[PDB]
Amino acid sequence: MTKLKAPAVLAYSRKINPTNALMFAVNWSDRDNTTAVMVGTKTVAGTQSVRGNPNDADKGNIQTVNFANLPHNKNTLLVKYNVKFVGDVFKAELGGGEYSNTLQTALENTDFGTLAYRYVYNIAAGRTLWRNRVGAESIETVITVNDQTFTFSDLLVNEFDEDVDVAEIADMVAGVLSGEGFVTLKVEHYMLLGEGSEVFPSQEFVENSKLSKQLFDLNGQAAMHDQKIGNAIRTIDTWYEDATTPIAVEPYGSVVRNGVAYRAGNKTDLFTLMDGAVNGKSLTEEDQMFVTANLIRGGVFGGG
Amino acid sequence: TKLKAPAVLAYSRKINPTNALMFAVNWSDRDNTTAVMVGTKTVAGTQSVRGNPNDADKGNIQTVNFANLPHNKNTLLVKYNVKFVGDVFKAELGGGEYSNTLQTALENTDFGTLAYRYVYNIAAGRTLWRNRVGAESIETVITVNDQTFTFSDLLVNEFDEDVDVAEIADMVAGVLSGEGFVTLKVEHYMLLGEGSEVFPSQEFVENSKLSKQLFDLNGQAAMHDQKIGNAIRTIDTWYEDATTPIAVEPYGSVVRNGVAYRAGNKTDLFTLMDGAVNGKSLTEEDQMFVTANLIRGGVFGG
Image (cartoon, rainbow over all chains, first blue to last red; front, top):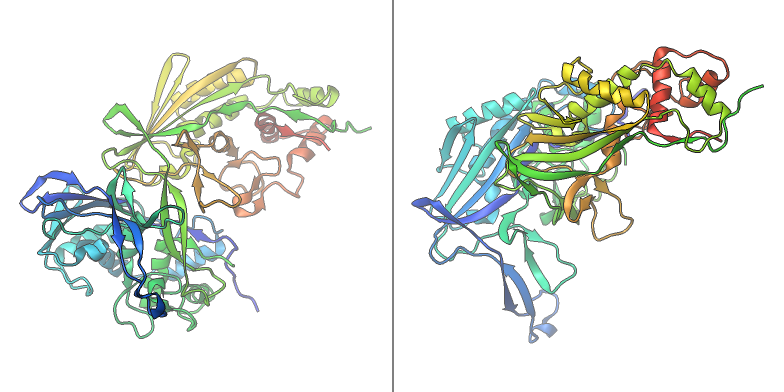
């Protein structure tokens, strides 16, 4: 007909830029004396309890793994990172002009307020802490932005409840996202897990060596990949078909650890909606939020 | 009839940057430099290609190189030197007549503008590429001939007039329009924030255990001298329908966007060179473009 197609190398750079997270040990009422949690190595002998075959059930299983605990005289895990939000979300890093420009035009009425609120809420509710949230006496999140400090505790993680301080931070974040500039939130999390509690750093892929589990380290200190924090932050999509709990923003709504994709094969993926928005079709408020959330995520959205 | 160009006519590059090293400092304690080291990390992602949604339920593991400022330093320090070398009309390999009449045809080239735009690309920090995004402030320090110059607040995409840029460009044009050489020694300080991702040059390795590999020198994150150089010679605003400056390439090629703003419309270096040697006249900006291609270096022969 006369359709406008996206260039082969249309690519957007990411706009939520978290750092790596470092993991320290403190006591809940002495947060100035911090000590780094160090990754160790231990032996693990196990059992061949795999569903398929009971003929191996009497055989052993010797492995060596990385592990990471709080020391036996500190009761609190402290997780530190920064999240820099950057503007100009609609200026493609690689794609040309025409397609991306009319896409920006089709997206200009996007509810940046809700996007920024859900981002900052995930940061404040401590979703970025993943399994470290489990079994915590209390959880205290501290976000410092523009020499201003905010503290959170009583936040439900899987609902975007309205909170006035989350809203005040989301105001600056949405100001940046819907326009130009950048703003850095400096984040600390305090979890009262108990002395000697196991902590959960990012895990590495070791295809070579004697380790079967390998934990992420920086100079030997337990740490979480910046991309894992980022994935937790963008868990804002409640708009896929038959949506229940929020999923991370992905062009196909993929959650690979569950082997499913909530936006694949039903014309609700990023590329279908994108080509619709460029070629005259109208987008919902939630569809515009989703397409803009993908433009914030970054990636190559070109013909492949 | 026509002065054909010798088959092996070639010029050597005249703007010689070094490789850039990447350190981490604090913005207000620049005498405590520590080096940024390239690391390796696992990265797990989704199969999110435009084509196939049938793989949208499948994941993928990779290992990649990565480079961060420490969590106790907030400023990236990029260091390099650039040596400008004169005799930009003496050919390296080509014979005599074509090169000599070309040297005569271009003795009225605006060397002031060339030197200014080179020095400006160095001072505005274009050479930093993606390390410019998200800076609270950028401070460039250029030392030359026992004279130190500091720059903050320079628009990268405009050649605004600046007195220090012009004063350095004066020596640079004195070398480029005559003989000799001169070394500018350049530092860039960027207030990015503690723990910020920094962007060294990327490598290509056919099949390796690494999916994405960063340029290192003894393990320290670094930038290729040719990338700094490509930023330095982004001065071409004279192709047809010119928006922003592009890097000086004989066909005005920008392979990252799959177009060549001087290919196939009698604006390429070879057409202009043939014209200049074979009697035809060039614009002032065309003389600038041809001399910039001679300063870039390369083979201009069959």
